[PDB]
Amino acid sequence: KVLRDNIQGITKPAIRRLARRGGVKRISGLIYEETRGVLKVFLENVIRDAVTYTEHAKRKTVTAMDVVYALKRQGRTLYGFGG
Amino acid sequence: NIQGITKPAIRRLARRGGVKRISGLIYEETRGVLKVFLENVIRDAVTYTEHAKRKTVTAMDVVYALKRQGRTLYGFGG
Amino acid sequence: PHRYRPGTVALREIRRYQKATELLIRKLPFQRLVREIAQDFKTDLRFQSAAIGALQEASEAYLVGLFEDTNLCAIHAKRVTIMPKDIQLARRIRGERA
Amino acid sequence: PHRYRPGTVALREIRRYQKATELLIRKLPFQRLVREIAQDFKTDLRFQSAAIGALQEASEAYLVGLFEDTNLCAIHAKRVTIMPKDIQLARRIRGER
Amino acid sequence: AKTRSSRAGLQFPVGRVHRLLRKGNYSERVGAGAPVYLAAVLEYLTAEILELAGNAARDNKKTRIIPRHLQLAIRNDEELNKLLGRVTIAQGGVLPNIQAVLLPK
Amino acid sequence: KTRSSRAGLQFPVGRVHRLLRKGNYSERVGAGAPVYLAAVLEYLTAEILELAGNAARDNKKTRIIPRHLQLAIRNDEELNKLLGRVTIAQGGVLPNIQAVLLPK
Amino acid sequence: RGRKESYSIYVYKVLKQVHPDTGISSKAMGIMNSFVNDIFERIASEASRLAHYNKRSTITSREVQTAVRLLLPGELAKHAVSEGTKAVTKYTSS
Amino acid sequence: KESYSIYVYKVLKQVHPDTGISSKAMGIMNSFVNDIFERIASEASRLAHYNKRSTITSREVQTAVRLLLPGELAKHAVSEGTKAVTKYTSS
DNA sequence: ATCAATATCCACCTGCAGATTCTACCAAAAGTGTATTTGGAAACTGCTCCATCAAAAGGCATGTTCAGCTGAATTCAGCTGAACATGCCTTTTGATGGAGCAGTTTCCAAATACACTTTTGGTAGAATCTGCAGGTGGATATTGAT
DNA sequence: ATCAATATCCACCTGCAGATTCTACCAAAAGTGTATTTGGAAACTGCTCCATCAAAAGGCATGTTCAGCTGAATTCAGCTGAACATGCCTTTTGATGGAGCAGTTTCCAAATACACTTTTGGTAGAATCTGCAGGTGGATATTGAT
């Protein structure tokens, strides 16, 4: 089945919740689009590297270690999945 | 000694940085940041000197030290 | 009826979501987004469940930290509403786009 | 007499020092500062001339980039004058604090 | 037969750290004191975190450390925060912190 | 009859191989790896020297100085990405005044 | 099959030392395992670089030592170097 | 004491046979070659370890270039590299 | 707008000296030929673990209304920081010349690799305790209107 | 300065999902006996590095005057938060096929290990040369004023 326009599933209320945990009280209306912008560039960058590991291992399944190595490369070191 | 970094030079640094107008409190704040910088870099560079059982900080010690801090510098050895 | 003034529930929510550690993006929509972004890179590849969970932990983590920095940029401009101008400054200083 | 309006010579200075690549801190006060700081970690240390020049290249570069980010914080707060809070915000966003 | 960990008085495996130093391609040869010293530093830092995390667990009235308590221990200690400044603790949350400017005047 | 000539390169493939074996990177070094790598280093060097030579021409000069190199790195987008955390000694900054700061 | 190692046996040992009443969830054990592996890597590779800068083919407890000095913020470094030297002298008393 | 000096001068004479290069600028090129070498070599090392491989091959160097170079710089790099390896094993 | 009078910028040519480039012979690589050793490509294959489905239910997302109060836009003055002309001194050269000291060899003792042959400590998967998650209702603050 | 209107404490209860313990294996750490190489330990140069020393020229410190920028104080259209009513779609749960990860072997092709042979890149003096730096002369940019 075809996958399209999926960044729109990052709901406006969920972007609000992320901003709350961030400590933000008032949120201008354009933020929700700006946030999705940033989020996509983040995921692209990470998934791109993550898949370069999957391809180098000649595999078809993106493993959690692939993501962990990828985040490490981007200086976003993640604990709690790493082995 | 840190007060030896004169305001006409901190002025020039902000000029190269693109700064048009400068608060008077800047110069003290700038000397503070610069001190934390040399402090961190030199502490590392000298740790490299001591490990190499030397008495002279070599330029490569400063380079390796700057790399550790993510301030990679070209033109002195690496 | 009752009515809380603009801001009171805002602060109620900051207090609430800062006390928690749950993920704030819905699992399925995030998973769809991730599979699309991956699909438009390599074709018919699988995902370990843990790798989508790693992507989501890292992503919510990233965005929440970006909101902290964004908020300080808004306060710094004597405002309380975060705007795109603020995010673009926060990222610019971080190095992420400059 | 003749006199330039406030703001004009500032932009003249920006256009000049961005055109140049010379170091902007006087060499000797800097050297004094470096050995003064190093004395606090190891005593009676000598420095390769290349290492004082490298430390100065690196730190002046650092400060110019910090001033760029500072200037942007000044602008962002509808100002033109950089203040200590601008430096403090720039460093806080960079991770240095 | 005595394990090197007990010979050095450690709970961490000195044999395993020594094996991980050769298989990791860090140096052509590995001295005999390196795995001991390293296993000691790792065991120390593990202890130092576990201490503060157990404390944070007790404060929340819990007997088992969850990722939150680990995040609390890391983020309230200045030096562990510096050491884990670019590290993200999954399921860890943030520290409660509301900017003063935003509070009910 | 060397290896660099066999690969049609100017960079030392033999020396790159020795630096890889001796760098403590892996137990064994494949035979094609140092070739491949020396090729990537030569290419990137060419790309920079090209752009910096244009900065040298454009500045009416014959000898490439650090300034021309920094102009070449920061005015080009992708080399800027690649050396974003590198400081080019004696390099200066790119001329750039924020519009907000200009007369009238 | 196939068996995969971790540090959980040792992290649990040190946990019952500092807080003998508390236990640890597996998600938090994974976070700890991640931390030991991260710091292992940081130390071993900074030490690798030390031995290489000084043209020495061997990483000794001294390389690990200044690696810790370089890499750990103070006081954590002081206390670390202390327990490390302690364990290495005690070791070499056969 | 070694350097990359004569090789940078050679490649300079290919692209710009008319122009020459300052000494400080040659040092900068040297630092650049050493840096890129380090980044690529160590990324390739990690590739090998992550997959429990014992040898660094051109396959690893390649995936290293993909990860490290912002393609399009990477596209041209991978080209220049496979090209030089193909010509090497021909002869 | 320009008219005028500062001062600033900008080429065009200039001549010398600090560096560049080019020559001229030597150890340390690097290429070569042969012999061993082996890392991981190739080929089945057990078998987790992933994609996908169905179904039901209630947790949240969507959209709409209404207005509190925030952000923007404005006016205004005190005052801070720029431009300068002034006056003095600290930085900058420039060898000079002695000396700490980073770099070199060369024995060889101590430390490490290494090749095998036992001897466990660790790990996977049963089995067996036990927090605490996620309901529940009281008491306690906290808000926000009158 | 009151009371309602709600939110947010907290403490208490209790089976179940996620620990903790209890187990045989067996991979790998440990013990021992040679083989290799390691990186100090004295012995001696040559560098670069400190250190005075001693003019000139800058480039800094400092005062004075005010242009104009930063903060404050207002005003207000309207954006964004709070509350709702609706009903969609995410979640939860449990089942099944099968792709493809990952444990085994098997066996060449490709790597390592010597051992000499051969070439190259680095040095340190010899033969150029680009560009700094300084010199007018002419448009340029800036800021006063009918």
Image (tube, coloured by chain):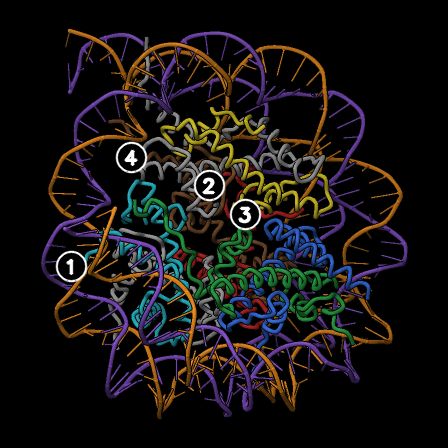
Chain colours: B yellow, C cyan, E green, F brown, G blue, H red, I purple, J orange
Kindly state the secondary structure of the residue where label 1 is placed: loop
Gap in angstroms between the C-alphas marked 2 and 3? 23 Å
- Name the residue type under label 3: Gln
- Name the residue type under label 1: Pro
- Name the residue type under label 4: Ala
Disc with the residue nearer the chain's start (2 vs 4) = 2
Check the picture and name the quadrant holding the N terminus of chain G.
bottom right
Question: Is any part of residue C91 visible from this angle?
Answer: no
Question: Is any part of residue B16 visible from this angle?
Answer: yes
Between E23 and B26, the residue placed more toward the observer is B26
- Name the residue type under label 2: Leu
Q: Which residue is mark 1?
A: C1
| Chain containing the residue with disc 4 | F
Kindly state the secondary structure of the residue where label 2 is placed: helix
* Image location (x, y in percent) of residue F31: 59, 66
Give the vertical position of I55 relative to J28 (above or below): below
Gap in angstroms between the C-alphas marked 2 and 4? 26 Å
